[PDB]
Amino acid sequence: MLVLGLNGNFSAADTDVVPQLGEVFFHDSAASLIRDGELVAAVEEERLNRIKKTTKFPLNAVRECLALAGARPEDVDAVGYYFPENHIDTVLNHLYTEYPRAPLRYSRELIRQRLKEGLGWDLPDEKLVYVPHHEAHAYSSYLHSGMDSALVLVLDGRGELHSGTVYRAEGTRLEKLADYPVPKSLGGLYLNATYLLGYGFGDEYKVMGLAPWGNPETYRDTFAKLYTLQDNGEYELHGNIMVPNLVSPLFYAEGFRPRRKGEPFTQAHRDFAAALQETVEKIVLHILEYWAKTSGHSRLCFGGGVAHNSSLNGLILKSGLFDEVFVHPASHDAGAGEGAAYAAAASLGTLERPGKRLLSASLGPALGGREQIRARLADWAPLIDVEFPDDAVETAAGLLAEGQVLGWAYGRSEFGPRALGHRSIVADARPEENRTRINAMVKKREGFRPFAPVVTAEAARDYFDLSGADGNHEFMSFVVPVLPERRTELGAVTHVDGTARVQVVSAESGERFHRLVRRFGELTGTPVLLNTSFNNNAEPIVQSLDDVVTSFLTTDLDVLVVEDCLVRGKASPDLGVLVPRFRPVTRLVERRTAGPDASAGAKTHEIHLDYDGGPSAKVSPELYELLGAVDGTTTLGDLAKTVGGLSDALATEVFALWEQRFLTLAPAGDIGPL
Amino acid sequence: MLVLGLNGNFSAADTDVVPQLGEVFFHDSAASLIRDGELVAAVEEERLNRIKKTTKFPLNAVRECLALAGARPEDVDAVGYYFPENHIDTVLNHLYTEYPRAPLRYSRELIRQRLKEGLGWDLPDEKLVYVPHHEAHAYSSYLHSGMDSALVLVLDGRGELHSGTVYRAEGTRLEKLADYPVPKSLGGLYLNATYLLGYGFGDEYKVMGLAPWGNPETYRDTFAKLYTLQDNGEYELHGNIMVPNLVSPLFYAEGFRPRRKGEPFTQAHRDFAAALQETVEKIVLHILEYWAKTSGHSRLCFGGGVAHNSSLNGLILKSGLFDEVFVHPASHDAGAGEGAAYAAAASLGTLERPGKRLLSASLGPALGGREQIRARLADWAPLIDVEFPDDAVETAAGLLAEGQVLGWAYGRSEFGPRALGHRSIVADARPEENRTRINAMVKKREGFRPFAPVVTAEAARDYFDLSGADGNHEFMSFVVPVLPERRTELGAVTHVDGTARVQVVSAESGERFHRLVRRFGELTGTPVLLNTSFNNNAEPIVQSLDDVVTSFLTTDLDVLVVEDCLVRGKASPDLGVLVPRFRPVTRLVERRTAGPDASAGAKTHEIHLDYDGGPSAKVSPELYELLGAVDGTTTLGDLAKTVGGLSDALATEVFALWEQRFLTLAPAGDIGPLADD
Ligand SMILES: COc1cc2cc(c1Cl)NC(=O)C[C@H](O)/C(C)=C/[C@H](C)[C@@H](O[C@](N)(O)OP(=O)(O)OC[C@H]1O[C@@H](n3cnc4c(N)ncnc43)[C@H](O)[C@@H]1O)CC(=O)[C@H](OC)/C=C/C=C(\C)C2
Ligand SMILES: COc1cc2cc(c1Cl)NC(=O)C[C@H](O)/C(C)=C/[C@H](C)[C@@H](O)CC(=O)[C@H](OC)/C=C/C=C(\C)C2
Ligand SMILES: NC(=O)OP(=O)(O)OC[C@H]1O[C@@H](n2cnc3c(N)ncnc32)[C@H](O)[C@@H]1O
Ligand SMILES: [Fe+3]
Ligand SMILES: [Fe+3]
């Protein structure tokens, strides 16, 4: 039994199903492969097309999952999709009425067209199974919990008809106990409030990271007008007929002005986040306190996108409601695509389930074999020096104790948004300056942002207060208090409220990462490391070896440890050996506007990425002429000859387009099949 | 007492408040001027920036209105805005949360800045009065009716809180009787249904025009699921949590598939439109039966964008519920902007009302004086031939009897969507072939589109059944039956169901136009002319002389009559003398896309208009080099020398771009400041 789980929209690589398709229309595209009830491969398409939270069809992710399982398309028994057929088709139909040129191609045709053109796979209609959205979520959260009975809560933005569902799980059987309608969505509320702080979709864990810095008293009574806790676990949210945002009209009325991009976060902003975070905690625990005593379950699985609110999770944990809580590492819509596979298996036959709680998220493609990795790093020789230590883990621990900030790339990439020892950036967790520098120089992000610690399983309770229910901490699902007497020791990973979004690494969850953290503690007295995700501000988590090296050279990391190799940047790196290649979304424009006296304005030159929310950048006339000559095989040095050679000015300008990922710069060739 | 009325959004000429601002966010921008209670001036901004139903701030319209009234900006005593301040500023706030780089400027700051930068007018804060949206509509519709009391129904898409409002009007007082919430919008219902026919915002009247071609029984039981008539004049519309459209999910579930661009209208399309039109009539008649009995009133003023549904208006007329029915020529938001002026006068002091019923929509800027018109037509000499007849009306009447289609441009331009004898295209109404002749070869639009007749006040009742009630027919607000014994005589202007959207021109509403139609009737025994708007598919109704000449040269009209001058197109017109100018929204672009093997794709060159829903067109490398050198003074022929000269190929390509209005092509200079009459 081999079943493919699918989620996302149906856009090709270079175009969208309608032009400029909005970024929220079936996002977080991914493919999951389960076989005999075990989850053998999972990767979000964002890692492969390099578009964060992409909507495009997860074609590459399917191909990558088939390869990791050693399977051909013909070997797959069923395909699940994380929404009912009528719902996705009605939304497609709506997009079509707004874009009268788009052909009427609905989801069944589009899935079968993508799989046939992109993999040579004629999917039979009988094998494609559509699935209720929260049923998919619930399966994913619950079957990977290691529990035989539980209460499953699914809260997200919305499914086909509900914003929240409560399930009873026993064995492999789900039983609905409750749902909440779409206009009560807590993910809708949280996204709605997020737009008031200059953020947009995807930024909601920044708002959650800002809330501890604020006082939830200021706007407590303002938010109180937007919801009412009712009896027997019910609640109402209170809408308006002004704008499609639940939060802005009332806060506008009260003098609150939405933050602009590039403006500092004022104390009024910090208090807003705090009040928002408190509201959602109040409602969810209201729901949970009720359904805990009503259904009788002492164990909770929490899924849906809202279950990535680690702060909420840490408060469910510290409440007394449950003895055991489980959260999947992908609880957002990519997790729901995995669930669709389990739900498809159950509709055609019986449902095989995992036999242990999921401990590792390391489920994507790997970097390659020892020899193709060494061969590909040779192709980067004009930019990097490489060492091969006897014990890279031992060497990396020493470098970490010397104050070096490392990139750490090993094995298969992490499914879900957190890095857990396979595509990580790590540093000493003790100096509070490391939070300031890694925020401002490395990840190039907002100073208020916290940093998550990884601690060994054996020293966890020496540092963090895990009391209350037993939660799973392998995937950074829970915010926990740092023990008061350790807060100054762990200055980089302790937040303003004394909490941390902790990962507890064990030999069974990540053997090599546990080795790194244990050996660091033997050298320093502190088996705790700072562990942020290995990506700059312009990209999702790095996937391939070329991704890892590109990101290392274009961020300000000290050393890269990739599959036992020690990589450092060359003194004077030679950008001219690198082969420029357009991304399928890369676009070059020469534009003239109206000018003074109804004239043609002066020319400008822009590179941009052709998707909703995609960035853009001005380029010189010289580089505009250079990038126009890109053929995918000629190096940047030989291309630059047609504008008179690769001057230092041009290489710097290219280096900045590279850092914003406007196009691919990598040595000739590629690593080859893994 | 001099009051400015404003409506629309606050975008500049060359950008929008937020980028690519949606075409629905405060549309049909217009300025209006009332002095001592009379509407002295009013033009929609679309006429001046040439963007149909534009949302941009109506700064030009304001300047035109001040000049037609001989007023300094500092002479204005109050400015009125057609929405309340919390509402527009809350919508702006929402646009600002979705575009976090947009400066936080709300409506009061934005109105003042457009008037200080654009006119030098430091607007005092105490002069700006914001007005409830259906209150503005109501004033416009009732103060021009000539009625001393009436029931007022305002039914549009949306105001701050309502989608329909019912008033009692006595003298100058409005008294609210009822309302319907936003989710019951019939305007919204109609626009939702328009999207399923491959059309969009601004095409509703096309959908109304298609409805007679179809049988409302096919989808009658399907629409019945979307609404319910209730007691006490209430109705419910039945939503869904699937998509922001009331109609599409149910029809998708029953196999209805929305029309694509360029597809022919199938019988199911025609039936859908018919069933859609039958529903809105049924509901609006259900509202009105109740409020005509309950208020007991015999006079009705109907306002809001839904009141441009002339089919609905005629059915209301043929119902025996009212004795009189009045409809303002601009019942869409441009009229709320006028009404906003009155409501500001009522708020700030006393409300002066119009003496008589409004008879003529001819409230815009005028073409110009006799001398400067002759001078400007001289600049156009390389492309046109011009005669100066002794009686142009008499010359025109014979031409029309001869079978020519005529451009007709006189005086001040018509407020509202209808052309009524000041910016019109006119032809013999008798031959049925003249429909496809003027549709397919002149307007260049769908052929099903029927054509409106203009009849004389004297002959009117000899051709149309104006019975049922006394409706005002000076603005084509009412569709009426054509008398069966005349339906064959009037072949170009009789729809498939026997009806017509009649203008009735009198010596009082439009003298010159009335003489024209009367004379043609003396020459033919049929005092009916076909009357359509003077504009091709890519522009609103023309405004300036250069607009009128441009439009004549880029359509296939036989003759143009413009202020007593007869203009025809030269055998070979000389495009080289026209001076190209960029419009503020013109963008010229060289584009490269991703190619195979991760390469750079092909350089495509294109011109486009940078506003939501604006057109675009591919251009040759040679025209791209030429257009990029446009300096706004040098002629096309002199610019063309930098690429080898204006070859016939380039002139054709430029001409096709001219025809789609991508840029302004016009002789050097302008007609100059429009002089005083
Ligand atoms: C113009 O036309 C329409 C317009 C609209 C609706 C429609 C139409 Cl047609 N009509 C339809 O039907 C939509 C259809 O159905 C659809 C696209 C459904 C997709 C699959 C659904 O995706 C899901 N299932 O919500 O994915 P999930 O990954 O689990 O979670 C994600 C949620 O969780 C929260 N969240 C994450 N992180 C934290 C944290 N750390 N703390 C607290 N909250 C957090 C997030 O904040 C977010 O709210 C997308 C969705 O919800 C949208 O906002 C993301 C609301 C979108 C609503 C609109 C655009 C108005
Ligand atoms: C994304 O943000 C949105 C989207 C919608 C609504 C609102 C908002 Cl903020 N909220 C309002 O309040 C709208 C406001 O009042 C407005 C533009 C009023 C003009 C003058 C009316 O004409 C609106 C209509 O009637 C329009 O049909 C032409 C249907 C529009 C529905 C929409 C534009 C859906
Ligand atoms: N704020 C606001 O809405 O302005 P507004 O007074 O100009 O009305 C526009 C509305 O009238 C509806 N509408 C326009 N023409 C229509 C027609 N011929 N039939 C029905 N509805 C129509 C249109 O589809 C849209 O819902
Ligand atoms: Fe979800
Ligand atoms: Fe309106």
Image: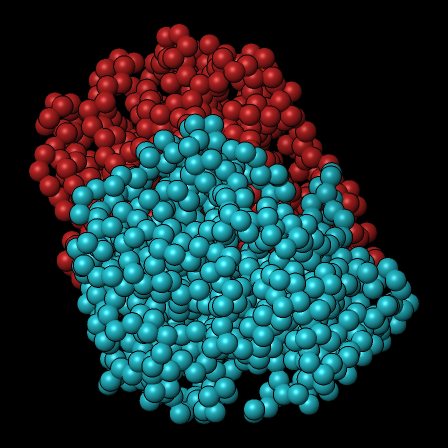
Chain colours: A red, B cyan
Which quadrant is the N terminus of chain B positioned in?
bottom left
Seen in the image, is B100 located left or right of residue B660?
A: left
Question: Which residue lies at the image location 16% right of the left edge and 41% below the top edge?
Answer: A235
Question: Which residue lies at the image location 51% right of the left edge and 33% below the top edge?
Answer: B268
In the foreground, B259 or A322: B259
Please identify the quarter of the rendering in which residue A656 is found. bottom right
Q: Is residue A464 above or below residue B126?
A: above
Which quadrant is the C terminus of chain B positioned in?
bottom right
Query: Residue B604, percent across and down?
Result: 74, 53
Q: Is residue A487 above or below residue A16?
A: below
In the foreground, B486 or A130: B486
Query: Residue B657, percent across and down?
Result: 73, 61
Question: Which residue lies at the image location 58% right of the left edge and 62% below the top edge?
Answer: B528
Seen in the image, is A439 located left or right of residue B224?
A: right
In the foreground, B104 or B331: B331
Question: Which residue lies at the image location 36% right of the left edge and 46% below the top edge?
Answer: B280
Query: Residue B87, percent across and down?
Result: 30, 64
Could you tell me how many numbered marks the image carries? 0
Query: Residue A669, percent across and down?
Result: 73, 36
Seen in the image, is B275 located left or right of residue B540?
A: left
Query: Is residue A120 something that shows in the picture?
Result: yes
Please identify the quarter of the rendering in which residue A105 is found. top right
Q: Is residue B576 above or below residue B464?
A: below
Residue at the extreme right: B644
Seen in the image, is A439 located left or right of residue B488?
A: left
Q: Is residue B294 above or below residue B584?
A: above
Query: Is residue A456 something that shows in the picture?
Result: no
